[PDB]
Length: 137
Ligand code: HEM
Ligand SMILES: O=[N+]([O-])c1ccc(O)cc1
Image (cartoon, rainbow, N blue to C red; front, side):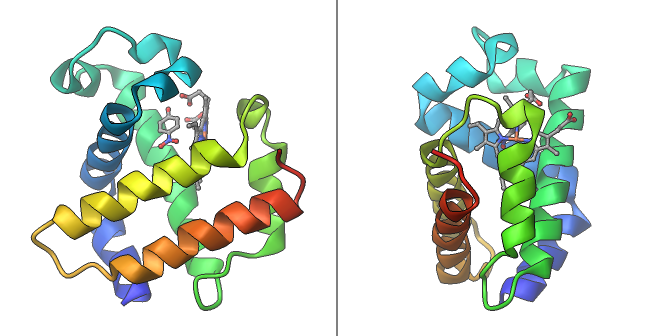
């Protein structure tokens, strides 16, 4: 289920984080707009950059914290607020997040492993909803 998936991802968080973010970037090329430093680089090139691995993991670490504090895949309002208020999220809208989780759910489904995809799909939708309630456009 969801709780076990959190453990699966945390277990090899660096690898999963990179794979899923890369799936995101490749599914939605315009999204690289929020990432000028990743432009014009293959997946393997990106993985060779120190900040790519470091940032992607720190992103997914916070995502797993938010996921774990959730109740029935509903994130805490305060976690949503944190994500809205982060300086690094200045220019973002809920659409950026919607797309991230569409990619994440697609990755899970295509994976050999028994991820609870429906739960992550709900988590993504409920996070988007919470981001909106916490004031993200
Ligand atoms: C639940 C989903 C997300 C979580 C938990 C999250 C968390 C974080 C964290 C912890 C950082 C700081 C990383 C660091 O400084 O090392 C960060 C930075 C950043 N995030 Fe988010 N993030 C999420 C979704 C997104 C999405 C969907 C986008 C855009 C599509 C985005 C855009 C950025 C940008 C532009 C930065 C600063 C530059 C960079 O680190 O590449 N974030 N995020
Ligand atoms: O998955 N994400 O949204 C990310 C991943 C890496 C990063 O540096 C910023 C955002």
